[PDB]
Image (cartoon, rainbow, N blue to C red):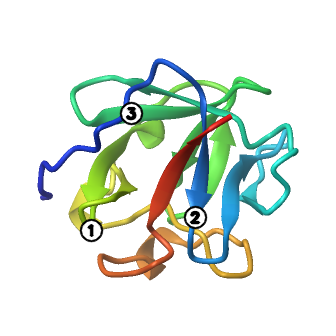
Amino acid sequence: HHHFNLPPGNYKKPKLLYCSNGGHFLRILPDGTVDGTRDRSDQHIQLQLSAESVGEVYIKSTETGQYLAMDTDGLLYGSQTPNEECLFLERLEENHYNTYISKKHAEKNWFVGLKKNGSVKRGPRTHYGQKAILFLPLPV
């Protein structure tokens, strides 16, 4: 369903997922809530990515051990255990950024995305060409 242009990074270290849309870092709160924060000091923005298959990743909270996931209704949530909803297709975009597509809902083009106000976008509201879907992985 999608291209195979991969980003040049690795999973050796944890990262911050910076969204240029509103300038927020992806955050997974202890209660499972998912959103964005501009506070670089936040303890819930440190994420550990790992590869399942080439270009297939898990995005986990280093702080809580929770996995980023997208539900049946396109909502992002923090999962205690890895499941099919936790896999994302990590790709290069605009020859620079990182995008994350819901593997489970790949055919629907549901991406991980942050609005300018720091709220997460619902899968069906996302789409190729948006700024909300563009992330820059930063060192922690």
Q: Which residue is mark 2?
A: 19
Does any portion of residue 48 appear in the rendered image? Answer: yes
Residue 25's place in the image compared with 114, above or below, is: above
Residue type marked 3: Val
Q: Which residue is mark 1?
A: 94
Residue 35 percent location from the top left of the image? 73, 60
Q: Which residue is mark 3?
A: 57
Q: Which mark is residue 84?
A: none
Residue 114 percent location from the top left of the image? 60, 70
Around disc 2, counting alpha carbons within 10 Å, would you say few (fewer than 14), some (14 to 19), or many (20 or more)? many
Which image quarter is the N terminus in? bottom left
Q: Toward which corner of the image does residue 65 lie, by quadrant?
A: top right
59 relative to 38 in the view: left or right: left
Q: Toward which corner of the image does residue 87 lie, by quadrant?
A: top left
Task: Write the residue at 24% across / 61% down.
Answer: 95
Q: Secondary structure at mark 1?
A: loop
Task: Write the residue at 38% across / 33% down.
Answer: 57
* Residues at marks 1 and 3 touching, judged by CB atoms closer than 8 Å: no
Which image quarter is the C terminus in? top right
For this rendering, which residue is in front, 117 or 87?
117
Task: Write the residue at 28% across / 44% down.
Answer: 7
